[PDB]
RNA sequence: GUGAAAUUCUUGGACCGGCGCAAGACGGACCAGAGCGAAAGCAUUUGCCAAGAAUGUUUUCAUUAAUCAAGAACGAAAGUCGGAGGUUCGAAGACGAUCAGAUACCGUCGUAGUUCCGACCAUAAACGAUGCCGACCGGCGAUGCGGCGGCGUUAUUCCCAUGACCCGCCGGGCAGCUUCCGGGAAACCAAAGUCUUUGGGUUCCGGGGGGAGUAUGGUUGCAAAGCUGAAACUUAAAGGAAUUGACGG
């Protein structure tokens, strides 16, 4: 127990990731070497604590976005996940369930009298409320 | 300062409610005010349920329960930790606490 | 609904409203004609009868009065009378 | 100096014909010496027994008093004395958010048995009931109670102690209450909770013999 | 005979055990099917000599074992049980010694029938002791 | 001092004053 | 029996268990932010006696109304008087414990009392610490009663009513949740809102804190006491609501 990173290392790791994202990578030993010159960190222990956390976040941001944000990452994430792009729209059903109350609503709208919608038998019982109180 | 809208008792359309007695100290407390706790207890506790079930002559016997309704004056309910003091906001909540079933 | 048109309330809420609370008072009770079975003539019966009504021919009881509206006994034909 | 268990003797108690099981169990009593008589000591003994003990596949929450009226040798003939529901059952039937109805009658049996019958019933909520509490109005309770009085006095006043006991073993009286009362207010938790005796027809010996036999 | 019946192996003998488990004392009382005749009665007060542990589970189980060996001495095998609290207007719950005495009887080579509560419950009692202000301690 | 017991003490003093005045 | 004990009851059977008998109290669970009543208050079944709200009403009368000095009926508990009854509980009192003390809290006993009838008393934190009548001003889900409707399930039957549910609506209620309506010192309140943009009608009633609900006068009461009700003198605060802290057996 007792390896929790503090806000000092945590925040500094996030800032250098955002400002220098392409110069970083998955290797800890290269990350600490770039951190030597991309920022002025006085202590060696603080330096490689920063680099160790940067390596951990690189392993995270490579497989999903985090609280930190990269402008290039945002555009790539919208560029990907374009759509499931089904061969047909998901809502072009040949038959659509329609209650008699909605069927007369479409008639009063004048847009009814179509073939795709089918009318169903209205449900009977009128019981739709949960019993009150405990159980 | 009025601490509770209902004055700590469930008396709205009445003028007087018959008193009942605290089971712990035997104190006259109105029936609408005392803390009521209907408790169902096993006749045989878990430490002896196996001994009784094994030693029983009957092949299949369900142990009966205890059906006693407990009335506590608020002093005794606080002392027995049946009811706990709550914050000003949490006081208004009237739902029973969860049974911790899952 | 600040700008509700009280000048012309729609009839579904006008019937919904209490009897005295409408824009103009209009009683809910009405007059209906009752045809005594086994008889020939037509008698006038209040829909909210308090007394037992018996048309002269029909010696049986026509309406059994209760709290709100009369109980038309079986075999009686009823019909409204001019709004 | 010596324990009385040396001079105690064991007698076996039997059951009336209403129950398919005869032997309830065994008792003990002191012997006969001087004025005190072993038969007289065993006279008037009440043995609370369970109907589950006396019956093969019937309910267990019903108990019977079964006083012994006569002893003949090592066997103690026993007739019906009273019934009572167990405390676990009668306490569990009292649920909140519903109305309890309690009735009590006094009936003279054709034989001469004066019985005090206590019946209890509870209102029933429906399957589609969304309202939390299923209460009964006071007039509904009065109608149900009065009807419960009369369809429980008719089942006993026109019959004998033999028929009444063998018909309350399956509690046909209670089911008669439920099916009649469902036209007014539906009930489910209806049982004859207790009966007790008040008067007896002068202790006829022949009636006990045909009670255990023909 | 010989401080017991002559019942064969097919049938067993049923006793009745009244466990009056209150606070400050616990009674275990074995009787016949009517309760008119008694076999043994042992209580914590006559088993512990501290005047405080009369209701302790330590004294209650010792009472249960003593009536158990006496019951086996009389050949009693089965035992319907009647648990009973103080009742009346006072407390309606069994004391500490109920479970210890119950467990001791089962583990002392005894057989158990039906356990039922004969606690006295008033329709509505008299004036309960303590005054209207309770027992201020 | 509790106002109820102040009231009771006042009642006792009023009885003393009535007794003194009656004697005179 | 208590925290631990003790006073106290016990070989005469104490306690326990069973069967009966008597007594006078008492009506659990069901019993709820549920009902009724002007409040106080009211809880086993049945009957009798009158009374009452709300709902229903295309009935009658036609302003007959609202609040009310004086006056009047009722009015928890305790208390007083007389007579019955005194189970339990229990002021006073005694004793045992505890304590430095313990006139107490705890335990045993027990008087008046607690119970019913009749006659008084007229006081409660008699509280919603919140006058009554009327008008208006948000929403929502419930619940009690009455009424009006509507898919359906269930009770019986050969058909409807009629009950038990389900979904709604109307009116009177006990209330509840929510809201930057508005108010308020705030706590909070759909009333404590419609208030410097101040006037719907009408009762009671307060004027810094004490002295003091005291003295005196009158009046009511068997009494205890009730109603009405000062002054001298003294004092710079007393208070209400919230905030932070400190502390809590
Ligand atoms: Mg406070
Ligand atoms: Mg009050
Ligand atoms: Mg002693
Ligand atoms: Mg009084
Ligand atoms: Mg008297
Ligand atoms: Mg006492
Ligand atoms: Mg006014
Ligand atoms: Mg002043
Ligand atoms: Zn208490």
Image (cartoon, helix red, strand yellow):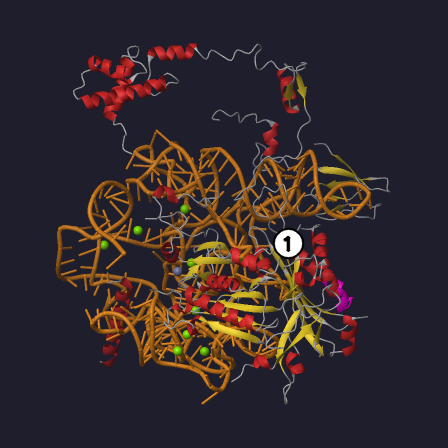
Please state the horizontal and vertical placement of residue D15, each as a whole percent of the image: 71, 69
Q: Nearer the viewer, residue G62 or B28?
A: B28
Query: For residue A74, what is the image quadrant?
Result: top left
Mark 1 C-beta closer than 8 Å to ligand 9: no
- Which residue is located at x 47 percent, y 45 percent? B99
Q: Quadrant of the C terminus of chain D?
A: bottom right
Mark 1 secondary-structure assignment:
loop
Q: Nearer the viewer, residue B48 or E85?
A: B48
Q: Decide: is A19 above or below G234.
A: above
Give the side of residue A104 with respect to residue A86, left or right. Answer: right
Please state the horizontal and vertical placement of residue D3, each as a whole percent of the image: 54, 81
- Which residue is located at x 48 percent, y 64 percent? E101
Q: Nearer the viewer, residue G124 or E76?
A: E76
Residue designated by label 1: D189
Q: Decide: is G147 above or below A108.
A: below
Residue reaching furthest to the bottom? D34
Please state the horizontal and vertical placement of residue D71, each as a whole percent of the image: 71, 78
Question: For the stretch drawn in magenta, what is the main secondary structure?
Answer: helix
Chain ID, mark 1: D
Please state the horizontal and vertical placement of residue D167, each as a whole percent of the image: 74, 61
Q: Decide: is D197 above or below A94.
A: below
Magenta residues, start to end: D152-163
Query: For residue D193, what is the image quadrant?
Result: bottom right
Residue D155: say if magenta. Answer: yes
Q: Is residue E93 visible?
A: no
Q: Is residue A46 visible?
A: yes
């Amino acid at each position: 127990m007792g390896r929790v990173r503090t806000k000092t290392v945590k925040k500094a790791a996030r800032v250098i990731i955002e400002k220098y994202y392409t110069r970083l990578g998955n290797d800890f030993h290269t990350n600490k070497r770039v951190c030597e010159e991309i920022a002025i960190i006085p202590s060696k222990k603080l330096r490689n604590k920063i680099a160790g956390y940067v390596t951990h976040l690189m392993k995270r941001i490579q497989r999903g976005p985090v609280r930190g944000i990269s402008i290039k990452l945002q555009e790539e994430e919208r560029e990907r996940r374009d759509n499931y792009v089904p061969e047909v729209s998901a809502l072009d059903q040949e038959i659509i369930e329609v209650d008699p109350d909605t069927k007369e609503m479409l008639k009063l709208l004048d847009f009814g009298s179509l073939s795709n919608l089918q009318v169903t038998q209205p449900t009977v019982g009128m019981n739709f409320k949960t019993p009150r109180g405990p159980v | 300062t009025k601490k509770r809208r209902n004055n700590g008792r469930a008396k709205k359309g009445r003028g007087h409610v018959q008193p009942i007695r605290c089971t712990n100290c035997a104190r006259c407390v109105p029936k609408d005010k005392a803390i009521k706790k209907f408790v169902i207890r096993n006749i045989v506790e878990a430490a002896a349920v196996r001994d009784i079930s094994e030693a029983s002559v009957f092949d299949a016997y369900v142990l009966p329960k205890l059906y006693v309704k407990l009335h506590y004056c608020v002093s005794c309910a606080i002392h027995s930790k049946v009811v706990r003091n709550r914050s000003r906001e949490a006081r208004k909540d009237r739902t029973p606490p969860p049974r911790f079933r899952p | 609904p600040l700008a509700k048109d009280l000048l012309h309330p729609s009839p579904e809420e006008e019937k919904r409203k209490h009897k005295k609370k409408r824009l103009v008072q209009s009683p809910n009770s009405y007059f209906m004609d009752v045809k005594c079975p086994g008889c020939y003539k037509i008698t006038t019966v209040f829909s909210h009868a308090q007394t037992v009504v018996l048309c002269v021919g029909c010696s049986t009881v026509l309406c059994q009065p209760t709290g709100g509206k009369a109980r038309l006994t079986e075999g009686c034909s009823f019909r409204r009378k001019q709004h | 100096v010596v324990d009385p268990f040396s001079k105690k003797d064991w007698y076996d108690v039997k059951a009336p014909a209403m129950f398919n099981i005869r032997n309830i169990g065994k008792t003990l009593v002191t012997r006969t010496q001087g004025t005190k008589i072993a038969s007289d000591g065993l006279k008037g003994r009440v043995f609370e027994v369970s109907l589950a003990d006396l019956q093969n596949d019937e309910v267990a929450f019903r108990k019977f008093k079964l006083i012994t009226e006569d002893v003949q040798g090592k066997n103690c003939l026993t007739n019906f004395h009273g019934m009572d529901l167990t405390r676990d059952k009668m306490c569990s039937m009292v649920k909140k958010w519903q109305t309890m109805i309690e009735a009590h009658v006094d009936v003279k049996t054709t034989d001469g048995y004066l019985l005090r019958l206590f019946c209890v019933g509870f209102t029933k909520k429906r399957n589609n009931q969304i309202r939390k509490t299923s209460y009964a109005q006071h007039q509904q309770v009065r109608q149900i109670r009065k009807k419960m009085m009369e369809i429980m006095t008719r089942e006993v006043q026109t019959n004998d102690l033999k028929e009444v006991v063998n018909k309350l073993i399956p509690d046909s009286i209670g089911k008669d209450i439920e099916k009649a009362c469902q036209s007014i207010y539906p009930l489910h938790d209806v049982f004859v909770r207790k009966v007790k005796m008040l008067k007896k027809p002068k202790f006829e010996l022949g009636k006990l013999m045909e009670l255990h036999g023909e | 005979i010989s401080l017991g019946p002559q019942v064969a192996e097919g049938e067993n003998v049923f006793g009745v055990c009244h466990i009056f488990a209150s606070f400050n004392d616990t009674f275990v009382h074995v009787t016949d099917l009517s309760g008119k005749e008694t076999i043994c009665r042992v209580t914590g007060g006559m088993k512990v000599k501290a005047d405080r542990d009369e209701s302790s589970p330590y004294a209650a189980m010792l009472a249960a074992q003593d009536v158990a060996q006496r019951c086996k001495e009389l050949g009693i095998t089965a035992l319907h049980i009647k648990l009973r609290a103080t009742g009346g207007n006072r407390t309606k719950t069994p004391g500490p010694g109920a479970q210890s005495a119950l467990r001791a009887l089962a583990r002392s080579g005894m057989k158990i029938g039906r356990i039922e509560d004969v606690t006295p419950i008033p329709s509505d009692s008299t004036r309960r002791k303590g005054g209207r202000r309770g027992r201020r301690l | 001092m509790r106002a109820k017991w102040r009231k009771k003490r006042m009642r006792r003093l009023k009885r003393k004053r009535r007794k003194m005045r009656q004697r005179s």
